[PDB]
Image 1: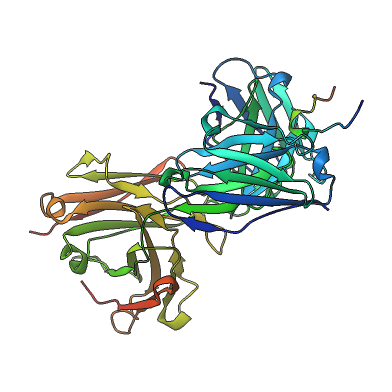
Image 2: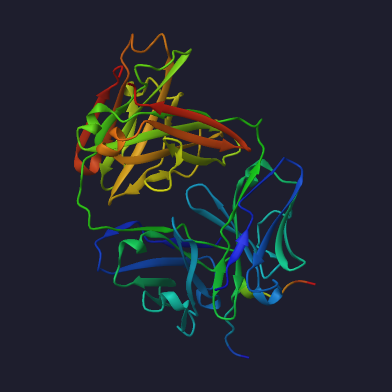
Length: 214
Length: 213
Length: 15
């Protein structure tokens, strides 16, 4: 079977360069072109270029000509893409694909950031004092200003999990922000303890917040 | 210059037939644009479907077929299955480069539709002490997984300082999202009413919080 | 003749 195995995730600082690999298996590597594609949040999918592995000739979209350099190693049947003068706008998921309507690699997540390791600040999300009581109550925890990803939020050492909703992170002001919520019966809070535990292994830090009525 | 446009979102049911289109801003789409179609499933999983207008990739179910309809490229799913719920992109060739469409979110109803549960939280006293203020609007348990979120302060539509996550699938196969309104401490204390408006299936629900007197 | 390198992205449509 065909396999397009890309190299792993990479974090670099602005101005550096990175070389992403794509190891082809299960077919004649030099018998097919190889494409490269970028997926970003603000620009969606963009075609970088393609390379003829037999001749080694690359072709680029005009806007990537000075950003990317495509090469191959015929001996290992691996295609390479080197990105130059990296900026934060180059942060994205990069794919190799033998053909756009066929086999794709699994993607390589590239993060370009000057930010340093930063623990999260955890803030409680609770209803206001003037809130109206209902059969249930929704609580949460705001996790702001951490880097790099990711965090793992746990509520009451895992006893609450069915009613948990943990949301994706967003990049804001060079740092990451996410939030998590849990819904419990009104008869359980504040009568009983509800705590969110936010683990951030990169900073070797964990922060627990006990939810209290505002 | 050449911009490719697809439908933002489409909904169908299991066993029905649905058609996705792909149009070019510069002119009609023809076989000279070699339309390719690719499917994205959650966690950046791309699977090619159609190459060269209508050549189905090996292993792709026969219910997927490509064609040209008028001046547009089309992907037709005859007898959609629940596992076809995904994002579908088209790519067109323009002489010397490819251009992707923005993608179409396809819902294949695997369960009854569900309205969103909306909860708006105020800035915590802890954050206000940092000279910052963030309002959080959590949205859960909506299906199909497409929503629009609008913020209003003192009745004025907000255009800056707000960001929303892309809908993410829940364990029960419904979707969830969260929206944030990032403000300065002074901005928070300088306005009265704050609102999060979430529209789903053309229905708008509202949650508001006003600074008590 | 020679070594043919394919780009399946650019197949001609079937008819």
